[PDB]
Amino acid sequence: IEGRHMELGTMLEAQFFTDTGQHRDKNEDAGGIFYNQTNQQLLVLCDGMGGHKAGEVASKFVTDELKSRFEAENLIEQHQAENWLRNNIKDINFQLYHYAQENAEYKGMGTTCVCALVFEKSVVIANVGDSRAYVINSRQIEQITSDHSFVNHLVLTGQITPEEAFTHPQRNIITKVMGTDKRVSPDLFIKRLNFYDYLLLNSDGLTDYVKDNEIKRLLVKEGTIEDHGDQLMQLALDNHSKDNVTFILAAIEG
Ligand SMILES: [Mn+2]
Ligand SMILES: [Mn+2]
Ligand SMILES: [Mn+2]
Ligand SMILES: [Mn+2]
């Protein structure tokens, strides 16, 4: 294959925030911020399904697998990041499928998974489920991923409006999730970091109770990344969120 130049290793100031919530008992969200041998940065977030058994086992499994595989890696080019994320996500899905099938305590477990590979100017995002990746600056908050949910299937087919989907009685249903099938087709995205201040990854425990406007205005205000994370978690709890709330906040600079 053709001669290509090595981009430098790049990372963003990113922090991981997770909370079980008062209303639930255990945290079935997992995730983390991991680095490979050349110090490339991978952000990982998983939402284990609460309606099924052992959501924390599934999310923890996918997270630990991605951490091990990525930390074992040396270099991933930008034009190969899509293949890397898709392949490893597929294999982890297969392993999680047989993991749930063979263990009777874990029968039917599953988890969402959104993850981002950070490069000098782009971010490569892979998504399976209704966890989200946003990009935010002073003027716009754009959701990069598309929810693999039923209500978003109705939205994308003109059957309901997004505002209707936010209060739809079946807004919890997931249509693509890890561990339920032998195969999975993850959604893959490339996003330019030119004109944005924040990359956000979050489970639905946040955005099921905090709309994009509130996130945008909270983030575009002044304050450090720790202050923004604290205020964002507290805003999720103030809007009476009753799921696990987890998000990675990544500050971007030119
Ligand atoms: Mn969950
Ligand atoms: Mn459970
Ligand atoms: Mn949901
Ligand atoms: Mn959730």
Image (cartoon, rainbow, N blue to C red):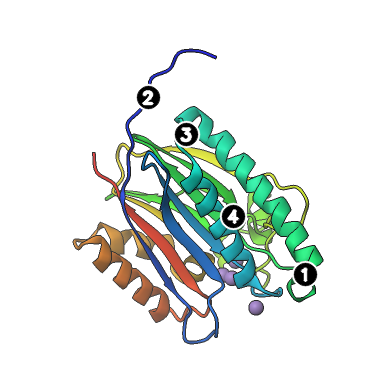
At mark 4, the secondary structure is loop
Q: Which residue is mark 3?
A: 76
Q: Amino acid at mark 4?
A: Asp
> Badge 2: few (under 14), some or many (20 or more) residues near its Cα, within 10 Å?
few
Dot 1 or dot 4: first in sequence order is 1
Q: Foreground residue, 202 or 89?
A: 89
Q: Amino acid at mark 3?
A: Ile
Q: Which residue is mark 1?
A: 103
Mark 4 or 2, closer to the camera = 2
Q: Which mark is residue 147?
A: 4
> Which quarter is ligand 2 in?
bottom right
At x 71%, y 54%, the residue is 95
Q: Are marks 4 and 2 in contact (CB under 8 Å)?
A: no
Q: Amino acid at mark 2?
A: Met
Drawn side of residue 187 relative to residue 70, left or right: right
Whether the residue under disc 4 has CB within 8 Å of ligand 3 = yes
Q: Which residue is mark 2?
A: 6
x, y (%) of residue 108? 76, 68
Mark 4 or 3, closer to the camera = 3
